[PDB]
Image (cartoon, rainbow, N blue to C red; front, side, top):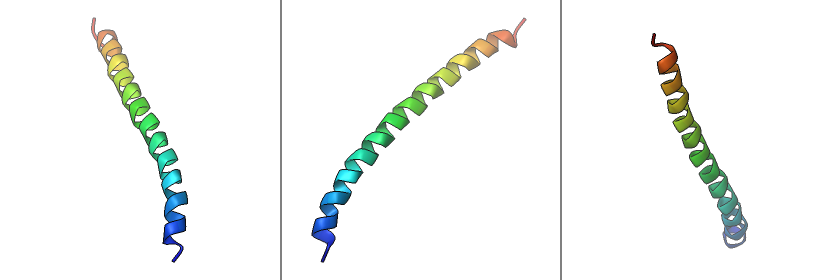
Length: 48
């Protein structure tokens, strides 16, 4: 028992955690792109 009840509450939590992960994965990836960006900048700074 309990599975049918908990599956409902847990899946709702799953929706939230999914969206949290999605926001994070795109944001970290964006910051990753920014990392490439700052790298590209520092690639000019490391040059003469």
